[PDB]
Each structure stands twice: as structure tokens, then as C-alpha cells.
Image (cartoon, rainbow, N blue to C red):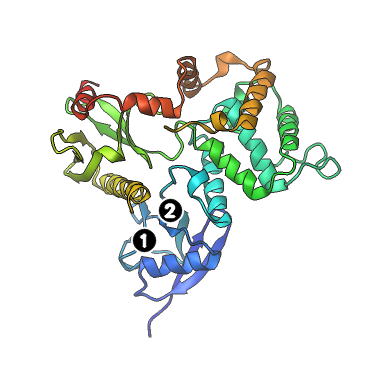
Amino acid sequence: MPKPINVRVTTMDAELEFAIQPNTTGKQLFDQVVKTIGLREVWYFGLHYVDNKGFPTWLKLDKKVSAQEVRKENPLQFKFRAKFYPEDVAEELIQDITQKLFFLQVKEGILSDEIYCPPETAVLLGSYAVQAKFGDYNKEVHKSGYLSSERLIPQRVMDQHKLTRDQWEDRIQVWHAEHRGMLKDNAMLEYLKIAQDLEMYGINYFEIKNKKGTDLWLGVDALGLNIYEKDDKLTPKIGFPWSEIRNISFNDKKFVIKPIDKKAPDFVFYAPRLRINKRILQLCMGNHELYMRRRKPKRITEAEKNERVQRQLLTLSSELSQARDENKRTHNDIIHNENMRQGRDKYKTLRQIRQGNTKQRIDEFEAL
């Protein structure tokens, strides 16, 4: 008789465990997961794991699980996570559950400093996260030390100020108090609205080279493709929006991006590993497809569209500058600050780097 396969899948805040048959496909597994947690916006998510060669991988849904070399272990371990991000969370996300999972996943990336976040923004987000978890601030309940166990802000942010842990608690509490009245769902959504303007938000980075062999980063996201210089992941230098892209493919380390303008030249770049190249290609195709479905079935920051959030950031900057230990800032801080000095934000930069012809942009790519 067919022996059942034990599988364990974790979401950002839940653990699921069930048995599947040897002939179970990824789709069958996937559907069981989403059905259990009540999630229907399935297009964003996937089952992530690490195969028996130590490689991070997304499960194929049209393919039996016991055929994709998942580690021979009991149970099989999967992580249910977002593989794709909406273009604008405020316009797209529908379900509380979907919002929450995005919120948790993005927050994890901020707190671990995988996603760069400037001090004031980090503090504010942390205060929205507190609201999301504890609800309304209550002096009777949330006495001094109620945040002591919390991972509130990135460690980098603490290092560059003259505040102690105890003092950071105080700071966040104050802003927690400002959010009084905000429902937890709305807290999480506001968290995402702010986070999505971050330079590194929603971006997968990959090491690539141009013709002459310059080490560069490729950035793949919901908006299009970005090119970065090797030491600056915050500021893309060249951009191609999905709207200018017709087709993505690769062959032996050579990527070829075909244009919608048949008169334009192909965008061509190089990437070393085959395993990595596969995931690059999936991320491009998936993001490209979602982009199209939104359009045929000038972005501004949250701060600029939400005067209340704008005032909060500004007030934060005021409170913090007096505690700022400037010779303790990191490389990304310094980069972010120069960008700000130049009057840049995520969307102004994207418009800037998308200027000119395809040929023109392809040429400066090679010149890098």
C-alpha cells in the first residue's frame, strides 16, 4: 500500500502539518495549504524550500512533490511565502489574511536589515507594528518595559544613535499612542503603504555582468528590471519597465530581453549559475505577467499622499537628530542620505533611470 508522506508547511505565523500521497503534485499540496488558512489571493504566493543540494527553491505546482529533490527528511519542510508583490498594496490587496502575511514577511525583512530602512521610517513602522500587535496603547496595561521582548527596529538604527534600549522603548511608545483608534488591519496596511516606498522593497537581487565584464546587480520586481552598480543596492542606474519588455529568456549564462518596439535592440546581460538563472527567469516571467493582467485583461510616496504620515516622519526626524551619532552610520545610510540630498525618492529615481531610448539605455549599460 502507498505510504503517506509527512509534510510540514509554515506561514509567517502558522504551522500546518498533514500527510500526502506519493503521487501528490505541488498544486494539490498548495491548494490544501491555502484552503486551510482561508487565503484566496493565491497568485502572490508559493511553497519555498531548500533542496538536497543546499539550494533555495520554489516548488513546481505542475509536478509531483516527490520528484523535485526535496531533502529526504521526515517531515518535508516548506515555507509558504509571497513570491510576488503587488504594484500598490493600497489598491490591490483584498483579504485580511493576505495583508497580514505580506505585513509579517516584509517586517521580517526590515528588522533583519535585508531591506534597508532609514531611521525615522524604521521607528515609525515599528510604531505601526506595535499598534498592529498590541492594539490601542493603554497606560494601565503597557507599563514601562512592555516592549522589552520586542524586535522594534533594525539593530543598525540603534547603533547610530546615543539612545539606550530603554530609551528606544520610550520613543516608540509615544508614537504607538498616536495611532490610537486605528484597527489592527489598518495598522498593517499602513505599515505596508510606507514600506513599499523603500528603495529595496519587493526587489530580488542577482549578480550579473555586461559585455565587458563589469560586476553589477540585476533587480527584478513588480515594476520592471533595474541595474545597480556593485556597491549600491539602493539606487538603480538604469531601468526597463515591463511595458517595454516583450520576452525574457536565457541560454548558457546569456540573458536576452526582447523589446515591445520591434525596431529596438535586445537587452542582453550575463549571469553565471544555471540554478540561479532558472529562478531569475521565473521571477521575470511571473512579474511581467501580473503587470500585464493589471493593464489589459506617476507614482508618489505614501508621505506625499498622506499628510498625517508626512507630519509623523518630520516630527520623528526632529526628535532624533539630537541623538544622531553620525560617524556610526553604515554604507547604506550614507547612500540614502546623498540620495535624499539630491531630492530623490524611489519613484523619481525610477523615472530618471527610465529616460531615453532602449538603445540609449542599453548603451550606458555596456558603458558601466
Count the numbered circles shown: 2
Task: Determine the residue positioned at 38% across, 64% down.
Answer: 72
Identify the image quadrant of the C terminus: top left
| Marker disc for residue 70 | 1
Horizontally, residue 19 falls left or right of residue 208, namely right
The x and y percentages for residue 104 are: 56, 47
Seen in the image, is 316 located left or right of residue 351? right
Where is residue 143, by image quadrant?
A: top right
- Which x, y percent locates residue 32? 47, 69
Q: Residue furthest bottom?
A: 1
Dividing the picture into quadrants, the one containing residue 328 is top right
Label 2 with label 1: CB-CB less than 8 Å: no
Asked whether 368 or 238 is in front, the reply is 238
Q: Nearer the viewer, residue 119 or 261?
A: 261
Provide the residue designation for mark 2: 44
Residue 123 visible in this rendered orientation of the protein: no
151 and 337: which is toward the camera: 337
Q: Earlier in the sequence, mark 2 or mark 1?
A: 2
| SS for callout 2 | helix
Q: Residue at x 46, y 37 (%)?
A: 201
Q: Amino acid at mark 1?
A: Val
x 16%, y 43%: residue? 252
Residue furthest to the right? 140
Amino acid, disc 2:
Tyr
Q: Horizontally, is 59 left or right of 129 in the view?
A: left
> In percent of the image, x 59 and y 41: which residue is there?
190
Regarding residue 186, the answer to whether it shows in the image is yes
Q: Is residue 170 above or below residue 131?
A: above
